[PDB]
Length: 268
Ligand SMILES: [Br-]
Ligand SMILES: [Br-]
Image (cartoon, rainbow, N blue to C red; front, side):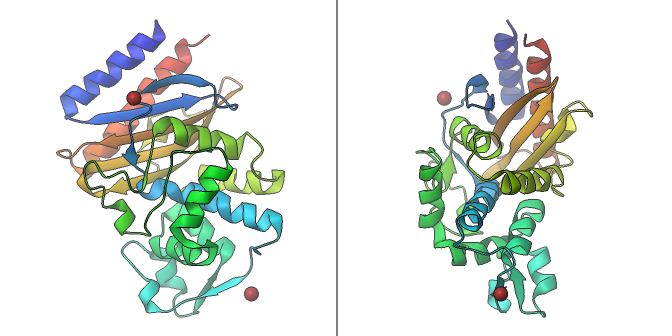
């Protein structure tokens, strides 16, 4: 069956690359299509910036936040990998929406932390996962320490299945207004950081949007959505490959994209 070949193809990559691959594919209602180590915890790394932007839009939707509110900051908000926050530093602020878009499409850490400083910190991020029916994902720290991915640490983790269901809830399951949903969907399609990861392994006519993440200790992740054969899906991929190079980890995730494609093409 297509599900056995999916598993054995992922196990081959896992053996040969000395890696662990967690994957969940769900339909728009969160129904499982396929998975592998789907309920093992993995560090979210930057993937949590997608749900963080969803949280931001829920606050906009409810009138407790305004997308063009200016958020002021100084040099101390600049951390590793803050390309847009660095550019906007002299101006002295980014708006809520500028920071959210940079968090999503550039994985900007300063922008992420600026939003966390506005929405009530890691506790409030965790509270939003619970609100949207995810009892698993948890943010405990800001960037970059939340990406430390110390082996066995449950802080700052999710599972493939919980996060795939979270993605589905946000894009398909009515969590946000239609306006807010469409905005975040387009940001994911226009993501700047995902060209060499999952989307590299999908057919070119599939509509795909995703958010990547990289952790210390070999974490490399990609979550998002794809539309194939008039069928919509949500997908979460988390991998741990301590001995691969960064480029090899990209290749690993693209290879997982290929394995997913083969399952979907085989699926009645
Ligand atoms: Br599992
Ligand atoms: Br303002």
